[PDB]
Length: 290
Ligand SMILES: COc1ccc(CC(=O)Nc2cn([C@H]3C[C@@H](O)C3)cn2)cc1
Image (cartoon, rainbow, N blue to C red; front, side, top):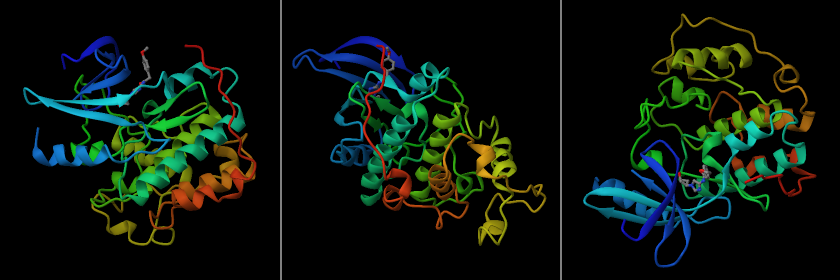
């Protein structure tokens, strides 16, 4: 750990804390996450091989005095801060589209390697001056676990959790990441979180109030899920034109497919990349004031 010079606290992610730091030998500026079971060590070691331009590179894994440090490529800003800074005028549609397109490329890559994120949220989406956006922390939830409260007692957000996770499916799939990304896509467009639940049942019921309480017609097998209760209120579905208003029919169609209830009907990252919404995708440069 002696090999790095801490510059500043970046934040309190899930898993421990994150600092901006400089490698004393290379001069490289990195992000150091302070998180150990052998199982976690081996799984974390395989993430070092998962390199893609839209995945935050894990540079090195350091285990000493049996604490764990993950060294990552550094990016100057996250999407949560960028959305907050863009709130008065909104992120231009072409930039929303580029960001969605790149995040689906990242997801398609990890998913083809059978690696899931499981806890996607705007804070783990990092951006640079060039117009790139990258996913951070892929594979970590499978390596260690995802808390109720962070290490700082901060409340882990439920806003982006897929309904099969909320209903107790133990063996959820790559579709949970598509759901979280859909929720993010909608938030970029409207400038308000889609489903801002403050409890697991509030999260589920906000989903139901917008997309309709799921049943056996739209989601075969849903009434047999572990946490499904027949006493759930039955709400009617709303139209997407009311849910993410400004967005055109190509975008609403894609969003609807990223938000299908049945994990098996939900679009894959690979199929989402071919959706007609990306017919005019481009790569604009964002306005970043660092
Ligand atoms: C000025 O204070 C900050 C500087 C940068 C940022 C954006 C950020 O979070 N940058 C980052 C984080 N990471 C790694 C840690 C692993 O979870 C992903 C790499 N770059 C936030 C705050």
